[PDB]
Amino acid sequence: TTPWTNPGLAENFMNSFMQGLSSMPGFTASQLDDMSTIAQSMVQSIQSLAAQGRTSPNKLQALNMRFASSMAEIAASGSLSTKTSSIASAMSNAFLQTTGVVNQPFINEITQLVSMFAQA
Ligand SMILES: [Br-]
Ligand SMILES: [Br-]
């Protein structure tokens, strides 16, 4: 479904995503640090919603939009496409490490949203 549905998977997935991304092209070392902050913010938002018994698919979706727009600010600052494709690759690898099943629609949606927010 979405790695955000379970607060524990959310954190494991995000950690693997950031671990993977650190070896990929497109981002400077300082941009990777900014991505990490964005990634922590997202995990924390998911976890806080869940802890308070306030989560819902629609709140999780809006957080995903905020997450992509935040990434896009960095991705838009190698090129946008090198960064976007690296995000997709690190996410794919993170799925394999965590769920063992790649959620390609999620990956594609993220790349789509990051590209969309960037061109604004
Ligand atoms: Br890794
Ligand atoms: Br409870």
Image: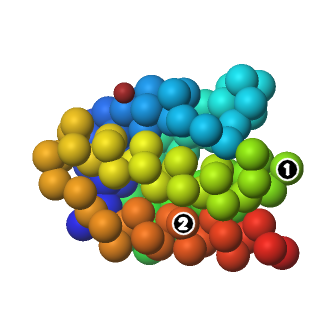
Q: Quadrant of residue 79?
A: bottom right
Please name the residue shown 22% across and 36% down the image.
97
Are the residues at dot 2 and dot 1 in contact (C-beta closer than 8 Å)? no
Q: Residues within 10 Å of mark 2 (few under 14, many from 20)?
A: many
The foreground one among 18 and 37 is 18
The disc at residue 110 is: none
**Colour scheme in the image?**
rainbow
Please name the residue shown 34% across and 51% down the image.
92
Vertical position of residue 25 compared to residue 116: above or below? above
The foreground one among 20 and 3 is 20
Image quadrant containing the N terminus? bottom left
Q: Position of residue 45 (x, y in %)?
A: 52, 45
Q: Quadrant of residue 93?
A: top left
Vertical position of residue 35 compared to residue 49: above or below? above
Query: What residue is shown with label 1?
Result: 77
Q: Secondary structure at mark 2?
A: helix
The disc at residue 111 is: 2
Q: Secondary structure at mark 1?
A: loop
Count of marks placed on residues: 2
Q: Label 2 CB, ligand 1: below 8 Å?
A: no
Q: Residues under labels 2 and 1: Cα distance?
A: 16 Å
**Relative to 38, 120 lies left or right:** right
Q: Amino acid at mark 2?
A: Thr
Q: Is any atom of residue 49 visible in this view?
A: no
Q: Position of residue 36 (x, y in %)?
A: 61, 31
**Relative to 48, 77 lies left or right:** right
Q: Amino acid at mark 1?
A: Ser
